[PDB]
Amino acid sequence: QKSASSLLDLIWLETILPKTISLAQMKMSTTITSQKGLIKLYFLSFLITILIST
Amino acid sequence: PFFDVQKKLGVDLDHWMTIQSAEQPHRIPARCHAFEKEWIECAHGIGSIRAEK
Amino acid sequence: LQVVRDHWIHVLVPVGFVFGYYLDRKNDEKLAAFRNKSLLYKRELKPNEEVTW
Amino acid sequence: MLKYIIPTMMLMPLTWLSKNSMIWINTTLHSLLISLTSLLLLNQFGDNSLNFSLTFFSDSLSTPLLILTMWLLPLMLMASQHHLSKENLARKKLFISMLILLQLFLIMTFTATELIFFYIMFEATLVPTLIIITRWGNQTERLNAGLYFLFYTLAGSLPLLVALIYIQNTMGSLNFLILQYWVQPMPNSWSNTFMWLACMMAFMVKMPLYGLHLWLPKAHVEAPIAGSMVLAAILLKLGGYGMMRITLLLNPITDFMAYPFIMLSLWGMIMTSSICLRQTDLKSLIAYSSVSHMALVIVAILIQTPWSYMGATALMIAHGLTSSMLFCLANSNYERVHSRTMILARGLQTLLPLMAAWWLLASLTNLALPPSINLIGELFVVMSTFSWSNITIILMGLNMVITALYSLYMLITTQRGKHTHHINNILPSFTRENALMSLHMLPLLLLSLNPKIILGPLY
Amino acid sequence: YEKNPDSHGYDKDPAVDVWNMRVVFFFGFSIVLVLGSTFVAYLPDYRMQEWARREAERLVKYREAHGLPLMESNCFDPSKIQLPED
Amino acid sequence: MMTGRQARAPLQFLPDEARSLPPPKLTDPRLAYIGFLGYCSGLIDNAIRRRPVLSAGLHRQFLYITSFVFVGYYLLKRQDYMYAVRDHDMFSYIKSHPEDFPEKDKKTYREVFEEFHPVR
Amino acid sequence: RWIARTFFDAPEKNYERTMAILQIESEKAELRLKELEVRRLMRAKGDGPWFQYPTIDKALIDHSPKATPDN
Amino acid sequence: KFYIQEPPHGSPNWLKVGLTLGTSAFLWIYLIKQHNEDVLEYKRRNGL
Amino acid sequence: MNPIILIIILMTVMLGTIIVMISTHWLLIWIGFEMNMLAIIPIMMKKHNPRATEASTKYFLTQSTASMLLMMAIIINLMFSGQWTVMKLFNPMASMLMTMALAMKLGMAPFHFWVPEVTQGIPLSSGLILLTWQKLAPMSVLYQILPSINLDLILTLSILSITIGGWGGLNQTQLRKIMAYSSIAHMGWMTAVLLYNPTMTLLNLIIYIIMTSTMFTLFMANSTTTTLSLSHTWNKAPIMTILVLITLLSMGGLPPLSGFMPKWMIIQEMTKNDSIILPTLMAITALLNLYFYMRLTYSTALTMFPSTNNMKMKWQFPTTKRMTLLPTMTVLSTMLLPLTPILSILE
Amino acid sequence: MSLVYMNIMMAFTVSLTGLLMYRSHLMSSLLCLEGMMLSLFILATLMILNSHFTLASMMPIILLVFAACEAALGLSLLVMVSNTYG
């Protein structure tokens, strides 16, 4: 029973570990104005590239 | 929420410069005028949904 | 009776049950249809009754 | 039904405007006066489920569960005092107000015809409970076990709305009456897969099946006794209830889709029934007990024999009163010595010689004693499941033996074997405790005479 | 640790307690338990099953006395019904 | 949607045509609940100002409640207008088009076949 | 007799009441499927009242006799 | 207590409340009259 | 600043947006945007700290260049068979550039980069006037030009707004930023439905305006730029806080509260059409925003565990700070779900 | 669309990519914006005067006036930004 319970809160701890490293999906931001601005401009022209063929 | 006041109060504001067929300062036909006349004659009372068609 | 002012706190919810109950009894009038018209139950209206219920 | 909706809504300002020291008197009084008419609610007869108004109606099952709720408020509120009995008036009127509003949304939920009104009122039921147990729960570190608890609910509990609205625009009306008679068979495939799984798991989060049962224990140790009797006497029966109704459709699907969940509940019944044997800290024992009986309920729901429902609903009510009461025993023991840990104190056959009878009596009613409604329901459920599989009785009756063992183990080592003699605090009983216990058992023993009230729609 | 001095004793702080046990013991034990227990003790025939007994008796007696086999199965007469075809 | 209907006479709140619709009775539960909503409004106002609530609410509370009854009343009226013209549009477009929406005869269960897997 | 007559309502009242509610919500559901059919069809046909996107108004075309050369 | 001054909201203003009750009378009776007349003309749109 | 000039400016902002709504000609609408910028630069910066200056600049660049891109699309409309009106654009491309332009005007996914920054820079009242009023014009244009909208774009920009903008705000302890990212999420919804049944878009617009209205107004009541400020106010006075939290849950769309109503109706008129998968793909992220906001709801309790609640800060004198219409909008954004048969009053 | 239109559009997009992909100097940003604005003036002029649609000839004028009272605003914010630091 400690196996199913520790595996249950270990899997939920794999979701919060996925929330821990999902904060990395938030921390994937480098907080650099030369990153999200110019990368959002290039990948925005890639929204007109994907929208060019979409 | 586009509102129509200028039809309600009965005042023209932008309707004069709107399309090529409006009365010009000293009436000079636009190049494509007559075809404006027929496109608006065709699409006048309809809903731009089937006016397309 | 006026002396209920002394107990005034209490009389509230009894008036609540009365109030809601009368609201259901009136509600039935809005729901009223098929009064004698259902196939199981059809009655020739009793001389003192223009209504089954 | 509206005659039951007004009087509690009027019971709100009764609380708010009042002289200090009379709030408990006024609320208790008028709330029991509600309970009378809750007992008026039984006209149910013949075949057609009575329909009060086109918005919401009552079949059988809604009627027993509802009677249990409106009965349960005055006893609950009656029990919650002396947990505090010191504060600013605003805390008291706020708390009683919250219990009221909670009851209101419960009545909404059980009576609700149309499943979207059922769902809105559903989460609208969950919020007040959350406010109760979190705002003051005695808060061991608080665990933050109210809030992400609400995330345990909504996480997979939201998409059932999606599936519903789908059912809405495909078939039109979501009225339950007309969803009946228009229900049409749904073949087994991958779309019906995600749908059935959506609705099922959506409710199955509430009555914990063994997979998700980590939900209850923390939330129920952090709950103040009022929030506990709210939680495990009712808020599981909401999930099982809505389950009862929405299983109307999903007709062939629930076989091939049911089987894994049935397996998991038949095994988890035994597992949970085991883990609840060895723990300390009494407040948890009755929790995992609730998990066990609710697993048995799910087992009863998926297999669709009518016997399964009769025993099922019987188990909803009987387990409601039993589990609720037994919690309130744990609390009445907790005010004496501040522990929550079972093994800490002992005795109480010597001391509190009366409180024995309520420990014993209640534990026996959770021991599945033959005339007790708990054994009526559990018995019919065992009959149904044995009809489904000739083999499963090994697991079922094994739950009989284990449930016997812990249910009768709780009766001891709290209540028997020695007085720890470094205590010298416990003050003998109360009249209030006896009032609470009595108000629990006495109806549970009387129902063991004329049960045909509490057996389900099919009867 | 507040406990009571246990001057007499009950639910709450003094002098309102007697009223408290009076309302809860009365409205709780007296009215609903005894009264209600008499109500639902015998209320009108519930689920109709008494009527079911009477009707069953009459109908069975008819079924034997007129010689028809009782309980014919077939919940709907095959005389009126249609069947799909291959 | 529906802007072709009401763009003929723009910014009519509700038209001279609407008066053929029965207006909501006083005691209509909606606008009454709106009155309650003004009650909790004023209550939260008297909570904002530190004064104990139920004081100053002689004129205030009445001002709130009556205001919401007013506004909410007109809103309900124009609402019922809106659903009126909606349903009208439906039925006219129904009748004017036989082919689009076929009227089929609903055959009785006498001809029906299903699978209906029993339990067992 | 006492209980039944004072506190309850005949299977009559309840029964036919359910007949009425089934009337109501019945025809509702039907007419809901109707409107979904309608609005489903309107974007294709554009015939009726619901979907109209105003074109430019012919009111002002200036029909007046103009500079002669043409048009 | 309150030796300091009369803080403005402390004592009532009987002109303001007079205007507010004015708004209550005007607004409310105007609503009632609106109801009566709309019901009347509604009766005119149809017949007995 | 002068207490007149603010009236003679705000009057011009109201005027500009009124022109964007009223005019049937493109060049006018373009002018209306120009006036809302020109006159909205003074409202921000009201206090002369540099934060408002740099932030007001970051608003000015992207907002103004957005306007210019709008003009470009208008002109391409003139190229292709064309006249100056407000109606379906005759170019697919002009519609593309115009959906991008109106996607800068109001915060959207590729273009949202400025909103959090500018919202924290400028003061409270400018925060209110930025995240609500100026948000009326672009929707009022999109409602018009929707027939030529390429579905794939606005659907995309909507989703990416919800995913990105919503997913953001996690580490943020600031308030203004939170209000920004939430603005971008409600954006993702309002624009998500835009093509199907715009009535719902105006609905979520109005409800949204009430939401941010009570929110910022409460931040004026208790002047708070952080959550720490929220807790410290909880130990100053409770009521304003629980109004802030309850309105935050209404900002999360929690079923009994009124914020659940736009989500719920959006799910109806979203899923009666064919695609059921996308709404769920929104509702997931909606849960994300939720339990973030409910982290901000474990910001509070009673018999609190230690928050370091300090002192001096009991006060004998009530505050006279004038709160304009707080109560009506508070109850109106909490209690509204028991309404909405009233939905159709809107359109 | 002739040629001149193609070319002026390419100028437009040169100005725009120059706007987004260089943040170094702010005056350069503001400038590139303004040059783009000029290109729009040129477009509207060439078109309107190509179709001999006379009553609309304002679009160059009134499009050009907001090229300034908005731009002037731009430079004022530039100065008030510079005096923060440098």
Image (cartoon, coloured by chain):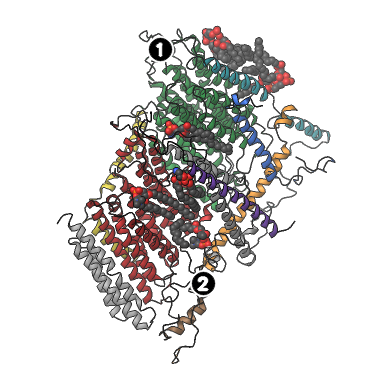
Chain colours: A yellow, B brown, C blue, D green, E cyan, G orange, H purple, I red
Mark toward the viewer: 2 or 1 = 2
Q: Amino acid at mark 1?
A: Arg
As drawn, D162 above or below D327: below
Q: Residue furthest right?
A: C47
Q: Which mark is residue B50?
A: 2
Q: Secondary structure at mark 2?
A: loop
Specify the quadrant of the image occupied by residue J74.
Answer: bottom left
Q: Secondary structure at mark 1?
A: loop
Cα–Cα span, label 2 and label 1: 86 Å
Foreground pick, F58 / D326 = F58
Residue under mark 1: which chain is it in?
D
Foreground pick, D213 / D281 = D281
Specify the quadrant of the image occupied by residue J80.
Answer: bottom left
As drawn, D425 above or below D110: above
Picture coordinates of residue D82, whole percent (x, y): 45, 20
Picture coordinates of residue D197, whole percent (x, y): 47, 44
Q: Which mark is residue A17?
A: none
Picture coordinates of residue B36, whole percent (x, y): 46, 81
Quarter of the figure with the C terminus of chain F: top right
The residue that label 1 is drawn on is D346
Q: Residue furthest bottom?
A: G69
Q: Amino acid at mark 2?
A: Arg
